[PDB]
Image (cartoon, rainbow, N blue to C red; front, side, top):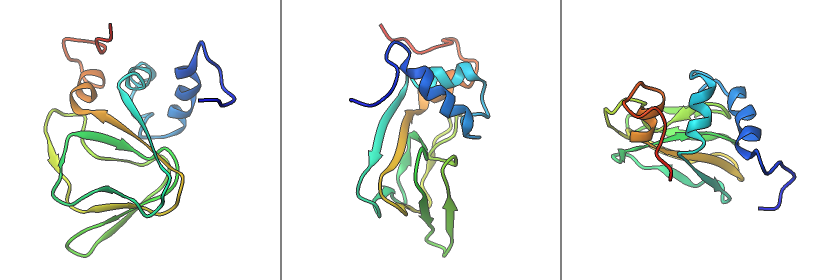
Length: 134
């Protein structure tokens, strides 16, 4: 990826942005940096794309990095989230099921996927402080 940004310390540059968002602020910095090491990089190019379907075993945490995402419910409700909001699963081992259909509102929408386990091994106080990457 050729883009104006530091190399030696890439995560750092990204961290600064993490703080900007509330969802990423709810947890101390350390947790943020750790997540960046256990979070996937994904960005939807074609707007109006489906992010999650109704009745799907949510096992990964999603966070709106850029763009707006609209959520639809089977009952007749439609939520509206904006850059900064979070959705997907909770930091608790407890799993959950999607109760609606998510769809982007604009193009060039960025997002991030984080495994539950790693999501409950950082924020929480599990035996392993950080992820094992070696």
